Amino acid sequence: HAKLVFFAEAAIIGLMV
Amino acid sequence: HAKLVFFAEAAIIGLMV
Amino acid sequence: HAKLVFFAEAAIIGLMV
Amino acid sequence: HAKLVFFAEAAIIGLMV
Amino acid sequence: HAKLVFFAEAAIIGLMV
Amino acid sequence: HAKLVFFAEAAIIGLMV
Ligand SMILES: [Cl-]
Ligand SMILES: [Cl-]
Ligand SMILES: [Cl-]
């Protein structure tokens, strides 16, 4: 499983950890 | 209120806590 | 890539077309 | 950068911190 | 289910059609 | 507002039309 964390600076980036 | 947490393994699952 | 499509009903379900 | 946190009570609200 | 539709302007707003 | 459109491939990419 991975957790999806969202960041932004505009484009939203969801990193799959 | 509930927080939406996202997990993945593909389908993304957003658990409403 | 795949298109990400979201549904809801609780828990959110995102599917990757 | 900002982190996107999701809350719900229905409308989903993504706060950009 | 409902379709989840996202908008942005900051804060993201997801609405459940 | 802008419409938020999501794609995936890993990392999710949300773009603001
Ligand atoms: Cl973690
Ligand atoms: Cl919590
Ligand atoms: Cl934080």
Image: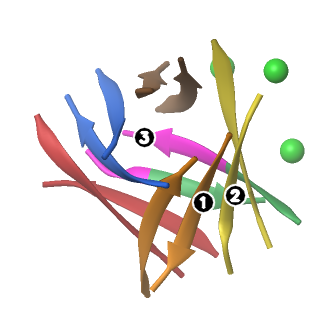
Chain colours: A brown, B green, C red, D yellow, E orange, F blue
Q: Are marks 3 and 1 on the same chain?
A: no
Location of residue B10 in the rendering, given as x and y in whole percent from the top left corner: 25, 44
Crowd band around label 3 with a 10 angstrom C-alpha radius: few (<14), some (14–19), many (20+): some
Nearest to the eye among marks 3 and 2: give it. 2
The outermost residue toward the top is: D1
Q: CA distance from mark 3 to mark 2?
A: 20 Å
Was residue B7 drawn as part of the magenta stretch in this picture?
Answer: yes
Check disc 1 and report the residue beneath it: E13
Q: Is B13 placed left or right of C15 in the picture? A: right
Check disc 2 and report the residue beneath it: D13
Check disc 3 and report the residue beneath it: B8
Q: Which residues are magenta?
A: B5-12
Q: CA distance from mark 3 to mark 1?
A: 22 Å
Q: Are marks 2 and 1 in contact (CB under 8 Å)?
A: yes
Which image quadrant shows ligand 2? top right
Residue plotted at (45% across, 21% down): A15
